[PDB]
Amino acid sequence: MQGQDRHMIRMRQLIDIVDQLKNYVNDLVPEFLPAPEDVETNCEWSAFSCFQKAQLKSANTGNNERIINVSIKKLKRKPPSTNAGRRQKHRLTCPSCDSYEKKPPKEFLERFKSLLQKMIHQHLSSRTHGSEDS
């Protein structure tokens, strides 16, 4: 009906900033950024950090540089406590974070935002499950 969950703000925000910074791809510097591809049910969390240390850097050439800083802030969002479990995990254990291969910013973003709305989202409520193309 009405209201705005605190958590949600983050979620949407994450996807927002992502899409926001994305729109400014022209201000995206190509660097080795960690992007967790396909994370365990309860891994995305441990991966959510891989998107933090990633450090979104803009081409910084004048345009959407300072603005990008708006995406970085959000992008650099902290996970829900620790990262993956506190008391020797629980639901299940997950491997390290920085393990997969790096990728570009355009992708790192198009992926991060997805990874979020992928698990994080559902993490709250499924909502018509069925996503797959490639």
Image (cartoon, rainbow, N blue to C red):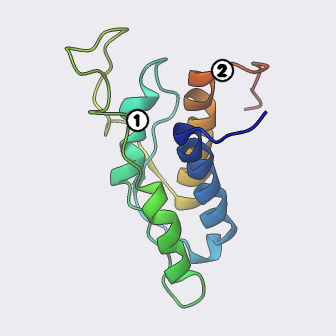
The disc at residue 1 is: none
Asked if one can make out residue 29 in the rendered structure from this viewpoint, the answer is no
Q: Which residue is mark 2?
A: 125
Check disc 2: other Cα within 10 Å, few if <14, some if 14-19, many if 20+: few
Which residue corresponds to the image point at 35% horizontal and 10% vertical from the top-left? 92
- Quadrant housing residue 130: top right
Which residue corresponds to the image point at 52% horizontal and 58% vertical from the top-left? 104
Disc 1, SS: helix
- The percent position of residue 14, horizontal first and vertical second, equals 56, 49
Quadrant holding the C terminus: top right
Disc 2 + disc 1, Cβ < 8 Å: no
| Residue type of the residue flagged with mark 2 | Ser
- Mark 2 and mark 1: Cα distance apart in space: 20 Å
Q: How many marks?
A: 2
Disc 2, SS: loop
- The percent position of residue 75, horizontal first and vertical second, equals 47, 56
- Quadrant housing residue 42: top left
Check disc 1: other Cα within 10 Å, few if <14, some if 14-19, many if 20+: many
- Compare residues 97 and 11 and report the one nearer the observer: 11
Q: Is residue 134 left or right of residue 96?
A: right
The first of marks 2 and 1 along the sequence is 1
Label 2 vs label 1, nearer the camera: 2
| Residue type of the residue flagged with mark 1 | Ala
